Image (cartoon, rainbow over the protein chains, first blue to last red):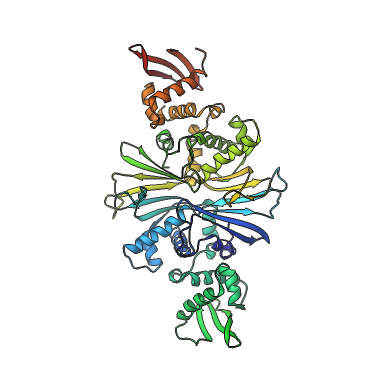
Length: 280
Length: 273
């Protein structure tokens, strides 16, 4: 459905903003040069961008186990792979993340579409999919009704049936989905930044971008003064004193970034991001 | 998998909304083996209603048909094959009604919560099992005219071809225990209450009372109407008030009324074969 290089492009615009409770969201996107709208629905709340890291933790544990579309996953393994203090509220936060993933539906409508598809020579293609086709869950205490009257459960083991097409891709194109276990422990914007590079920096040794374009390729819907302000703060604390306000370096797990601020009439209007790929 | 062929009328039929109803949630009690279980039904839009059972089983036969004229979990379905198998004259409003049925099936999610027990793989000393599932894992759909933004501001589409990815476990079960899910092409054209009766028989299969069939089929409608409706739909399928037979496509029924103080208080149903 979703190609692995298109992931940061299309799927990330289909998720809700962080800490946001939505049941629906519509977004315009581009692949194949073609206009397409993607819809995200849930009977509960849709996946937010903060769930990408629990989702990619599930990816890692799936491929590891199978080294048969049934996969058992212990919530303590998710908490450690995500660098979470085994707690009560922390178990519950992972559970809410996996829940939002389970019940989120994505529907991709091609718009300048027009293909030979069958009898229809100029068709309109839509693809509705879900990451998990079925979840079996073992809890330690009894199902309880919540405040709203619907059942609440607290799993500690999960049995995952991934969507068939994605499941064989998750094992075939295995490289596009297995991330360093520490990248799964970062803030959302660093995770989003690293993921864009795994696509962009294929068949490239070095390359230079502007943070304004990283604002476009990563988070079109967030204004500059907070995309830049946010991504710099997280990039600076991953820099460990290696630089000043106007220059710092950071080793984004193989991608070596050099972040130079750009100044016009004394104020900071952009940032140069120089990338150098330590082939590992 | 979860809903076996013996459990179908028990678990799935109670989990759907009543007809003519638009719901986003519904909770229901079921019995697997005498152990308590709750089933939850959710949709972002409306949940599958019992009137959708026939469209769902129309999808079942066409799925099994395709792969016997040819296991690969990708299946194409033309809306006209569905429209005819359900005996609907190809129309506009009729092709849109099938589209809505398939829509409710797509987005309806089922969650089965076991309530007592049960037994232990290990560090779960009295575990509690829940199963969340959806009939279709993925749908690819081809329309002839363009997506429009609708009344709600969200996209409306008018498909004529559907490519179905069934849930993996159910897809092999739809081919393993294949005999159950394959129905007579005329059963898919009847009223809901008749279809529910025929489906119950393939699970139960004998002598039954219409009073208990009222519980096994539609616990939520009181006898006064369940019998009046079902005894009418059954009589329109026969030739010949207190005694009649009807050949429910393989199950031949003999329906004897029970009379007490001049009025009819129940019905005995003999069933062969």
